[PDB]
Image (cartoon, rainbow, N blue to C red):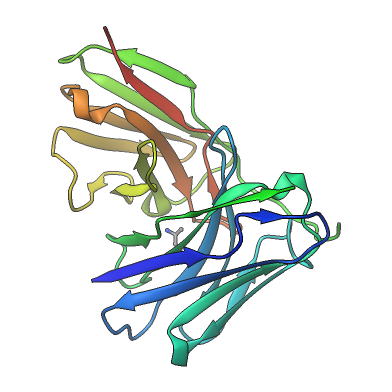
Length: 232
Ligand SMILES: C[C@H](N)Cc1ccccc1
């Protein structure tokens, strides 16, 4: 019911501001949060901030004084502005909509590529996904793990699948709930600092990257990712 599309320049010189736009389309919305998320080369995902339905914003301490996220409800649009960019800000940037009442679904944009041609202070939970890389055969039972640096609520640990050329799709919510579009051969489990995704029977189509994610504690964070391959 919701489509998001990111725009802006794909190249930027350092110190310039980055300005991006999220043109949000489709169905009317009575609450929720529009978030910006960025993905580096090598695929580390970075939760930047959000603006809510009521104009409330939240920024990742790591960005604090460089970032602003604004709205233009009349133009049905959300914006990202980031000051003093450097090469470290080279990423694919995504906007995404989520309804706090609707745990089960998340909307992501296409994602825009942006290449780049201080204060803050905070703490974050680290999420570790090992192996970095896995090859299993058609038919094999596969288990993916996510270990957190401190406890998180099991209700706010989530998994995403992503495929080359495309954006993370929500795969599992609240530890063990599969999302729409996910075959029931997948499962999830765990509690405290230890979570896993399971595929009872690996199929060729399941090879992709998997990211766990935590939003039990601010800022939200993603795991380093397990890339899952097929054999032969
Ligand atoms: C990343 C979360 N699934 C989305 C979210 C959650 C809470 C607030 C804002 C956005």
